[PDB]
Amino acid sequence: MFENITAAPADPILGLADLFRADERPGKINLGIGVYKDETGKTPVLTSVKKAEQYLLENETTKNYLGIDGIPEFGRCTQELLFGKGSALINDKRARTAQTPGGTGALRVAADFLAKNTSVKRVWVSNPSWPNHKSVFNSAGLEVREYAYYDAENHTLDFDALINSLNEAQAGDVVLFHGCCHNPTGIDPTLEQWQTLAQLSVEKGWLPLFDFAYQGFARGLEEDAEGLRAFAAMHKELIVASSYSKNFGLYNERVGACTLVAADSETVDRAFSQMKAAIRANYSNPPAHGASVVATILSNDALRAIWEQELTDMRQRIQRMRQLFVNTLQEKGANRDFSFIIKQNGMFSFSGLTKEQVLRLREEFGVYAVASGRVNVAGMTPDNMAPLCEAIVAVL
Amino acid sequence: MFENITAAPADPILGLADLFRADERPGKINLGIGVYKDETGKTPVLTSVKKAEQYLLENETTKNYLGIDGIPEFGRCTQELLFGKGSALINDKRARTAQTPGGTGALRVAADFLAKNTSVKRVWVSNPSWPNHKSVFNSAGLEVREYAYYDAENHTLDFDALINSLNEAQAGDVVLFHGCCHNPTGIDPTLEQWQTLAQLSVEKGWLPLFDFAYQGFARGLEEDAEGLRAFAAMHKELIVASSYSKNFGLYNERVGACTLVAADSETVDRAFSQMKAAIRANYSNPPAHGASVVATILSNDALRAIWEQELTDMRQRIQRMRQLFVNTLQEKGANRDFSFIIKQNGMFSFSGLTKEQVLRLREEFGVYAVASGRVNVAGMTPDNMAPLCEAIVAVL
Ligand SMILES: Cc1ncc(COP(=O)(O)O)c(CN[C@H](CCC(=O)O)C(=O)O)c1O
Ligand SMILES: Cc1ncc(COP(=O)(O)O)c(CN[C@H](CCC(=O)O)C(=O)O)c1O
């Protein structure tokens, strides 16, 4: 039976880590997967996290199953982070949050939930976008359409093309938005643009689905949440899939949340029971460790102050690297203007390189980037910056 | 869009956990969820586990993404436990193992893998079986069919009704088998019977899918895999979904594995690539903590030895309770013979109690059991034995 199975190609992002760990030429540089690295080129576990893990080691007395929707405090803390402490959505209890296995896990339960319990037939995702978005929704039988987003000429948001592109998005259709730090462009809407979209969304009757994987990597925790909060203030229903993989450096512990919002408590509770059913038929209940760490940190003011500082330091080093990247490109002889990089938010930067050039950097200079030209700025250091820029320049 | 979603019914097993936690009675007894309890009625963290966690805390340097199929050593360690160190399967590199979030997650990926890449349309599950089996398969789009298995009149396995039932299973169909400690009956086939079903399996042309969540709870690690091993020696292809929730007391860390077996190394690798695709579109990659604990214990002879001792102690305590349960029932004046209970394997026991009786135990006596009459013997202790048996006799 397994003979008739056709091999699947490598993941355009995770496949990368395999090739990288394979070639043996010295000096190779990895700018693929979206993981943070400090100035030494390592992805350390945060201090606040190590602290929380010791607390857990000392006070944990059982690994007994969590409820299908996870740790109660985890759910509460994520809603405050998303909508704000005094938020009306919370006070009126219009939101229920399920702890999931990473941001990916949250998108999948949201997809299963929609496919099996609603009349949703189509999901609109930005072009370009995180590659796995289409795979997740397709796995639930949902048709995925794309809408315009990036102005490849001006290196800005093509807002007119975006609006025009979504003209055919029907009422009942789901529209996917990146909370902040758009992957892979690094270009997010302004608050005014978010407000325009929120209004457009209600009038057309779209079901907004927010992918929030980098809260705090643009400007700050609250600031990065402005777009989402502009929608939540005007929408009856909406879904937000968030991830703690990045802002807590907990990649492999798989910590995420799928937050469901309905018109009133009675409706959200009813629909949430169906979401739990979807979870039960998938992985049953969520892994405790990562989520426990997070709930511990967000609940203790001492740890919370620590973590916030560590997050601030990560954001800052990334921005510092962005300026260093542009300066060194010039220094090494690039005639093309890369100033636009300084305007992009988050870990990534859409370089502009072509699939041909990205392939040259890899096989010829041992520099790894994703085939779409996306390069991970969080992976650049004062030590590989020069070799890196010299490679890019040689391929331009 | 969420206005007309009908509420879902509570899970027949996880739902009870909520009712129990809420129950105000101070004398309430929990025999519902399949969770182990020690002599004091607690679900402790194994000492082997606690030590492994201590190591991880002081030696883990990064939380970097853990590869789609998880920790390599983990995969290798689960293959030896399932097939034996010097297995031809392992030597001929015919097996590929993916670390998954629990046994349930392993079952879901297998289902997604089959529905998306093969011609498989129906899965055969024993009647009775774990209630969530049907839910996992229906969710992936597969239809679920039941085969006879239990002789309620003799509290024994109906080998003739079983084989007479699977006659309707066409070629290309999947048949679900419980490695050992069948849930909820506790009655497993003898090696002889395993030999038969195996040969019958290859002949009728079925794809065997084993659910292995209790390895070590029937007789021992090696002994409980006999049935599986008999199948592996004859089949070209097979799927095994295992769990470490129970034998490592790591329920909430979600530690399981999905193992694919094919005719040769070329075929399995090609097939495994699609399984990784199914995983990538579900939760992307597995949670490291739980899996890391198992890997470090199974890899360290000293820890390994401690763990096996603890597992032996859990198994024997359950057997002791099994015997005590039957002796106490008579002592309390049971109007029947529960001698068959001594012949059951694992954590459970199919009491024979009716749904009405089970409801009565909960409401009037605060004793919680599954509505199917399944009782968790591992949840019984020298302290709650008397109150418990008095409750059952009162409903008899
Ligand atoms: C927009 C976006 N959504 C969801 C996720 C999923 O997060 P989690 O790992 O919690 O499930 C990522 C991770 N960004 C990827 C990391 C590697 C990958 O999974 O491809 C990246 O853009 O490199 C992401 O950028
Ligand atoms: C046959 C069987 N398969 C799969 C599982 C899944 O285990 P994991 O938690 O690794 O995904 C269990 C757990 N036995 C259940 C535990 C509670 C539940 O999930 O219903 C039980 O029968 O009580 C099981 O008995």
Image (tube, coloured by chain):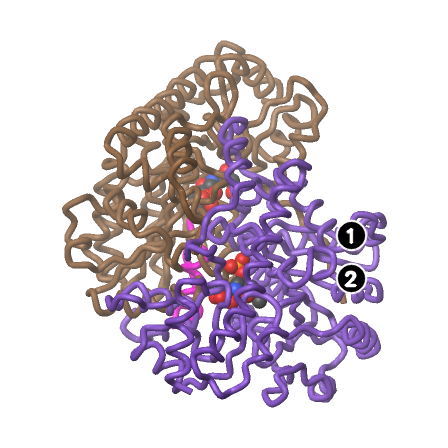
Chain colours: A purple, B brown
Could you tell me which chain the residue with mark 1 belongs to? A
User: Ligand 1: does it lie within 8 Å of the C-beta at label 1?
Assistant: no
Q: In the rendered image, which residue does mark 2 sit on? A: A229
Residue drawn 35% across the image and 51% down it: B71
Q: Residue furthest front?
A: A331
The residue shown at (41%, 41%) is B150
Q: Is residue B202 left or right of residue B110?
A: left
Which image quadrant: the C terminus of chain B?
Answer: top right
Q: Secondary structure at mark 1?
A: loop
Numbered label attached to residue B385 = none
Q: Are marks 1 and 2 in contact (CB under 8 Å)?
A: yes
In front of the other: B291 or B78: B291
- The disc numbered 2 marks a residue on which chain? A
Q: Amino acid at mark 1?
A: Gly
Position of residue A394 relative to residue B38, above or below, is below
Q: Which image quadrant: the N terminus of chain B? A: bottom right
Q: Nearer the viewer, residue B199 or A109?
A: A109
Outermost residue on the top side: it is B331
Say which amino acid is labelled 2.
Arg
Magenta stretch in the rendered image: B107-129
Position of residue A311 relative to residue B30, above or below, is below
* Label 2 secondary element: helix
